[PDB]
Amino acid sequence: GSHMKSEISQVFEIALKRNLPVNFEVARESGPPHMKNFVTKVSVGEFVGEGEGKSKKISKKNAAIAVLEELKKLPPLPAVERVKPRIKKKTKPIVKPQTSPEYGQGINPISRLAQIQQAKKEKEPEYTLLTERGLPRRREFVMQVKVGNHTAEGTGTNKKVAKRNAAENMLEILGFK
RNA sequence: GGCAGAAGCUGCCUCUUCGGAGGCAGUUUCUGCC
């Protein structure tokens, strides 16, 4: 074996200890301001990479793989100090996840609702925040969303997670379920 | 040739009145968009 499920996920947090990786940026300066980036590049340490790969019909992380080879040629680092202890801690990844020989367009309410908006020539719903609460012994997120004439609500730990809990209602409020 | 959104996986950042909260991105599988 020579690859994993993610490879940009390696580059992405080494930036915390190297202060030069994860510098993803545009590849042009005479068109991207119009509406969309339409090509991307990355710089890491003393090197640089681009999304092209062999043809991009291979992966969507050729940009990072082309610069992750420089993370193997790094200095001793005379700045941003670190440690590497052993025989004192142990860890293991999760084993609950699974795979399938097939896929679908409605695996969960959350993806399903987001996927339906694009088929209507939209992008996303009209999400909103309420959080009209703050008791001496109770605090929580309270999301609101609108889709035309109706609304749903949900709970979470940030504005990228309360979207999950509300989506179970988002199909039943407007009659998609 | 090429990008953005959602979920699953990965991990980071800050606050706490001691209930707990607030904030991010990446990838990959679906979709749409270039």
Image (cartoon, coloured by chain):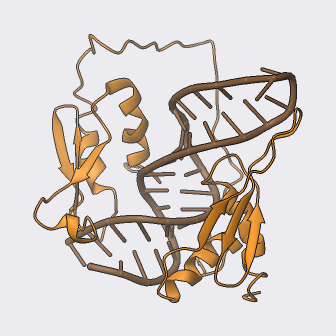
Question: In this image, B4 relative to B12: left or right?
Answer: left
Q: In this view, which residue lies farthest toward the front?
A: A132
Taking B12 as reference, is B18 above or below it?
above
Q: Is residue A108 visible?
A: no
Query: The chain drawn brown is chain what?
Result: B
Q: Quadrant of the C terminus of chain A?
A: bottom right
Quarter of the image where one finds residue B27: bottom left
Q: Is residue A163 above or below residue A125?
A: above
Q: Is residue A53 above or below residue A15?
A: below
Q: Residue at x 10, y 64 (%)?
A: A30
Residue positioned 20% across, 65% down in the render: A32
The location of residue A85, given as percent across then percent down, is 52, 12
B26 or A160, nearer to the observer = A160
Q: Position of residue A41 (x, y in %)?
A: 21, 53
Where residue B1 sits, quadrant-wise, is bottom left
A145 relative position to A69: left or right:
right
Residue located 40% across and 28% down the image? A16
Q: Is residue A26 left or right of residue A144?
A: left
> Which x, y percent locates residue A93?
63, 40
Outermost residue on the left side: it is A30
Percent x, y of residue A172: 79, 82
Residue sitting at x 77%, y 81%: A173
Label count reads 0
Q: Colour of chain A?
A: orange
Q: Nearer the viewer, residue A156 or A19?
A: A156
Q: Is residue A154 visible in the rendered structure shown here?
A: yes
